[PDB]
Structures are given as structure tokens and as C-alpha cells.
Length: 48
Length: 48
Image (cartoon, rainbow over all chains, first blue to last red; front, side, top):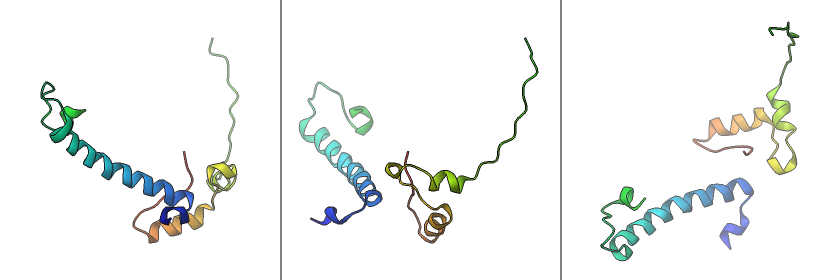
């Protein structure tokens, strides 16, 4: 409901914010919980 | 091949450029948006 009250500039700002916070979280989760051992991923750079 | 070129001078007002953007591009008054952006620590106006 709260995001529905935003204008287009605010919506773009919000989405940019969330996507950046979100990828950090997903990347962290992935490396420790999902990444297969075969892939020698130690950090976010390796994940890329 | 070095033909003499026509030499043309054209004056461009950016306020008109921004004010005149199509509605879908977020047209704006340049002076007003600058005031807001300067007062704020961040933000943006327009798009693309």
C-alpha cells in the first residue's frame, strides 16, 4: 500500500534502493547457502 | 575535398529544452528544480 502513494520519481528512487539492498542480500545468501562447491566462489566478485 | 562550409551560430536555452520535453519524459522548470535539488542533499529531475 505504501509504495502506491509514490510519484514516478519516488518510485524510481525506491526501486533503485531496493534493488541494491536486495542484491547484496541475495548474493550473500547464495554464496553461503546455494553456491555449489565446484564453483570456487569466495566473494561477491567471484559470484559475478 | 575541403569545400567551404557554412558557418552557423545557434543559441540554445536549456530551460526551454527541459520545459519542452514530452510529458512522458518528465518536463520541468529548470530553475525550480535546481532550487529544490540544491536545498536537498540529493534527488533528480527529468529522465533519460
